[PDB]
Length: 87
Length: 217
Image (cartoon, rainbow over all chains, first blue to last red; front, side):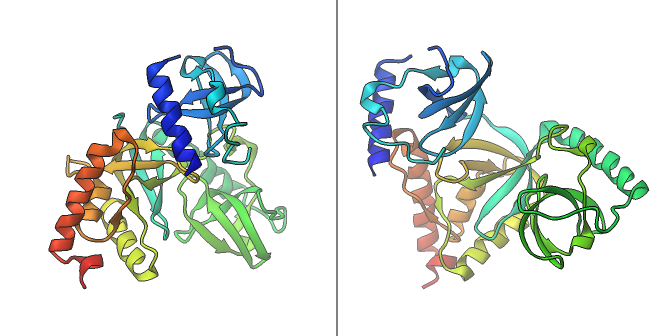
């Protein structure tokens, strides 16, 4: 799928260019508990240790430290492929 | 990726998903239930101080005659209210006379819903109802209402996909279903799953040769 292709490309890029200031509404990459990176949006900033993100392609939500966030490169923005899950 | 968390598996669904509780918070849950059940015994819900609406929390009196935290899903009629037991994962249709108000002392703010839904990584849920029942039955027999180790493998459109390990190093639960011919392998393409997928496909070849279950004919 477009999504699988994008994820492969993005992961490649992150492993070649490993990673940010979280703000409500801002796009990012987020490292999930599987240790892998996904596209996300910052939904709520409760504190540095507690950023509430939404995984824009999968629909899951998670509170995590901002140390597990990074910039989403223009090559993997929502213009390239829209969020695959409904926020 | 390998971070194994001890979980208590509480419910296997007919779609071969399952609900687990984090062993860490088990005692807090235990305390809450005893506190809540004492309250309910002193202050039994009166009809009809509770009006069921989709989305609304409640207490529900389960088939063991005990009360649990729940959330209302479909309301068919006052005799038929669909509820979801938030700490365990099972669902039930009950009359409004077996429901009550969930008082704030025992709310999700005091202690969050304790059950989380997961699916097995690397396998296909059988589409045939009979085959799927056979797979669910194997999982119910082997892990339902027991402690397991859980490792999150990846995100998915629905709940995350995980592997489970039996207690006493008996091995990978999903892989065991493959070895028994009860489920087929989902061939993941991601690089980090190459080795595990090879392991699963080999198990599946073994089930095929032995002509087990799905491979009977």
